[PDB]
Length: 125
Image (cartoon, rainbow, N blue to C red; front, side, top):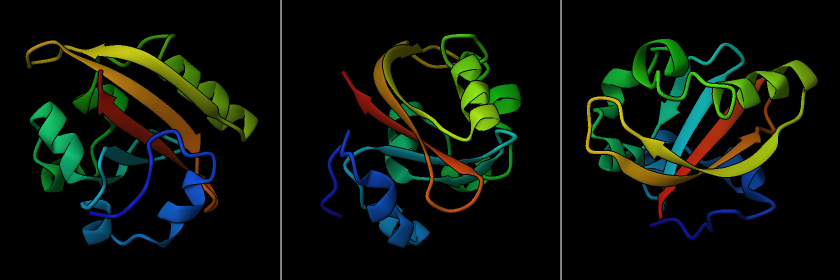
């Protein structure tokens, strides 16, 4: 288990070093998204929270295909302003209900260090 804390101000930096194996070590859910919302990375914790088989979700669109319940102004819309601005750092509660028991979560979005990618982090509440 990689020692990283959910909400950590420096988190994009710590994660810059992690391969997919190491990402599967975190205490929370981790997704890396492209500017278009396609899934670059996806860890074992998020699988665990949502049910989804990670390896299979890589390459799909988060907002169109996989998580259409986030296709809202409170979630997706927040995302696309952030890609449009080149800056994004937001944290909110949210309920995940697509083809699953409704699961209340806490979500943090942050823009990556690397060029044009974006992190979605997830934990139970």
